[PDB]
Length: 295
Length: 297
Figure 1 (tube, rainbow over the protein chains, first blue to last red):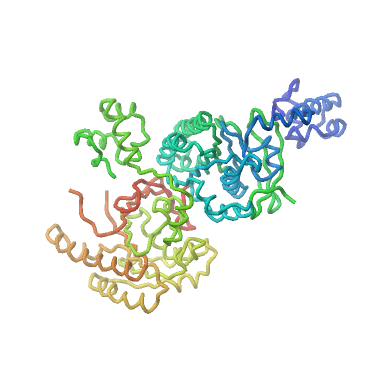
Figure 2: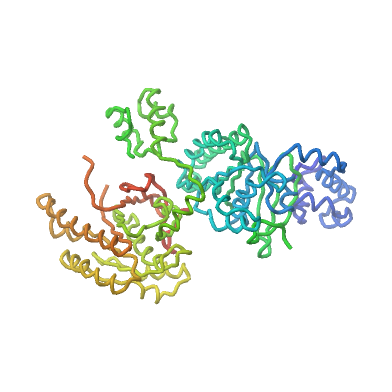
């Protein structure tokens, strides 16, 4: 589980005293001292040691054998982000048969991330990829054929071959965005090499062509349908769908990661929504080489 | 393009589609045959067709990232300030060609002209062409202030910005004509100019040749004037923008590209491609800010 509010045998009254004391994340609780938590939250010592137990337990730490672990890695295939940190957070990388969302303020690293993945995807399972192609649906004109270049170089790959494996299409508005997605089903069947679908800023045009709280219902109706569509595609055709949303509540997306800007080059990525992923934030950086770990 | 051009479709339904509010193909391409059948009062079987034929009509082609990059070094455009509007115009106002912006008073034509008479000076990295502009002012619309604000928002030098904009009042058609004539010198004297802006080209003609009595000659003259500005843009590799103020059988027009602007909820505005060879039809929305021309929300 995630979030404190979901802590077992816990009163909803202390849940405040915990968030009023600055204890928002479970991983922060998991390692706190019962004593200091008792004093800082103004809660009975006996209960501190409990929410800390419940919190640590919520992390799901499992000491597997080196063999058993090796077994599970061949059992599954993911695209690596380029940052072991971020990968770890994501239990390996971007999964197929599923849609992952990356949301956050402008410049949090969501774009770079999209590009980065539109390249690693082409790499072989040994180096972090899936020997496949990518479809980059460009919603707001963010694609930097330059950024794909640097990323490419640093990998010792062939710039032009890299660019040749990235299907590109600008989506000028919702109607076109919807259509483009609709014709996707053919593409994937026409070229089963495709493994990565990237729709940067999916919600974007909708908030634009359906502004205000007056359209809220239709905006969601239309968007949810657009998303339920991309999800299926990913599932049926065994590929990974990635979408980024740019924010500053009844979501469809499977996995949701939030990105935040940190001291200059650095950035933080946290698992918000996810069924199989354990909560926690990790730190990575935006380099020229691409998406790497900090320091 | 356009609905009346839909294959195997009766001209009878073409009306129930325009009377139901389905003007553009892109609106059809994503509608529900079901709802379309109720809204237009058309056989369910015909709806799913109009939509099939409509979706096909959008011309969706999944090009390779490489071929696209090739097309970018091949051409250079001026950015409108709204990534929306630029998307609609496949990058921006193109050179070697004339683009018209027409619409009711306040649709954003003016703002747009000013915004372009500044973005033109920006370097290719920021969306410009590191060039100057000629602003032929037909009805006294230039706002030395509006250039200022737009200028600031770009962290540019007010003074310098204004020094890279050639300005000239064109009091009547005859002067408008002369002015354009002498343009050939200017562009040759100063090859840095890259944006010609004639706001309200048709204006003086409609005034000096009013009524349905002169319409023929009014257009004979105006079209000759436009063919003129077009050539200039082509020959001297620059961009000519003209704006026309209209209020709201395939009619003949000279202008390469034509976009219609409409007012929307207060701040917002809609821009749609009407005439265009290489531009795919569809309307997008943008807004009028103090900063200048930007996207909405």
